[PDB]
Image (cartoon, rainbow over all chains, first blue to last red; front, side):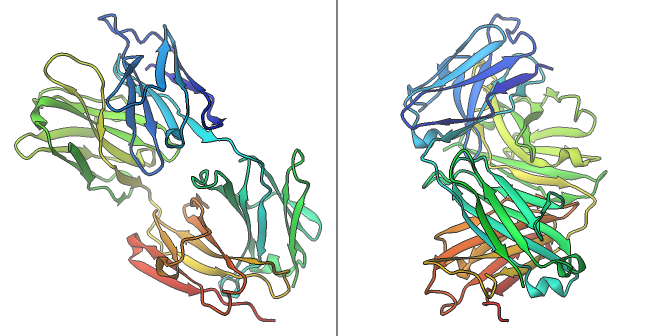
Length: 216
Length: 225
C-alpha cells in the first residue's frame, strides 16, 4: 500500500494570503501508463469531500484559479492563493494510481485572528446528579484564540490531572474563536470530602492566569 | 443534478451483519464504476470497495476482503454493500461515490459523493442519556452576561440533539463534541444569555436521543442555599 503523509496537520492563514499543503508518498505513484493520478479533495464540516485538483495539476469544474497543484515523484504540493473564508476546512490528497487507492491524513486550514482570552465559568455538580452517586464538576472556556490553552484543576489547592475530560469545538465561522469544556468526574463521596474547586485557564504567552472557583 | 443517497446504517454487535444501500439519480448509472469509502472517528478516509459499470469486476483492500461484498443493480439504479462479521474497526461514516466512466478516457476518480450513512459496530448496549442542569452557584459574581449549561452524560450510541428553548435560542450557544468515557458518550452544551433575561425568564435545554427513543426537557433553575 502507498502511504500518503500530509503536513502540516493544522495551518492557520490570514485571509488573503497563501497556503502550502504537502503530501508525500512511500513509493512511486506513476501508473504503468506514465501518468500520475494524484487528486486533492476539500472537506467542509458536515459536508462530503469535493474534488479540487485531479491528475496532479488540473482544476476540476467550478474550482477557482487560486488553487494550483504541482509536484514530481513522491512529493506533491497544493498552493492556495487569496484564501477566502469558504476555503477553510480539511484538505486530503488522494492517489488513484495503484490499488488500493489511499488517502492522506488530511490538513486543517484554519483562519488567523487577534488574540482573545477565554470567558471562564465553573459549575458545581447539580443536586440531581448527587442523588445518583456521581458528581461532575464542569468548566467552560469560551471564545478564545488561539486553539492552544492549558487548563488546570485544583481541589483544596492541590492540583488534579486525573479523570479529566476535555473537548474542543471547531473554529467558530462567524468570529474564528475556539471554545472548550473541561469536566472533572468524581464520585459523590469524593466530592463531599472537599471544599474548594478551582478551574484555571493559562496563557503566558498572552493574558496571565484566569481563575474561577466555587466552595459550598 | 446528479445525486447519491446512502441508507441502511445503524448499530450492530460485533460479528453481526448489515446491508448498506446507495441510490443514484440524474445520470446513466450502468456506465459508471462505483465505490464505497469510509470515514473513521479519527477523520481518516479509506477506500473500501469498487464495482464496474457492468457488475463483472469488483475489488477490495485486504482489510475488508472476504467480509464485504459490493453489489449493484443497474435496472433499479442501486448500489449495495453487504457487510458481515463486523468489528469495532468498521465503525465509520460510509460514503458512496462514483469514479470513472467506462468509456475513454480515465481521469478524476470520485467526483460525486453521497452524504454518508453511519455504521457503528459495538457490544455496548443502547443507553439513554442523563441530563443535568448547569446553573451558577448561589454566591458567584454576576456580570452583564450569564452562562448556563446542560450536561448530557452516559449515553449510547451517537448522536444526540441539544437545543435551547425548543430552538428559539441559538445565539451564544456552544455544543461540544461528545467524548467516550469508557463505552459511554458524554457531551455538554453551553448557552450565554443577558443577565436580566435569567432567571426572570425561563431557560430550558432539550435533549433528544433517537436510538433510545428518548427526549428530555430540563429547566435551568437558580440554585438555592
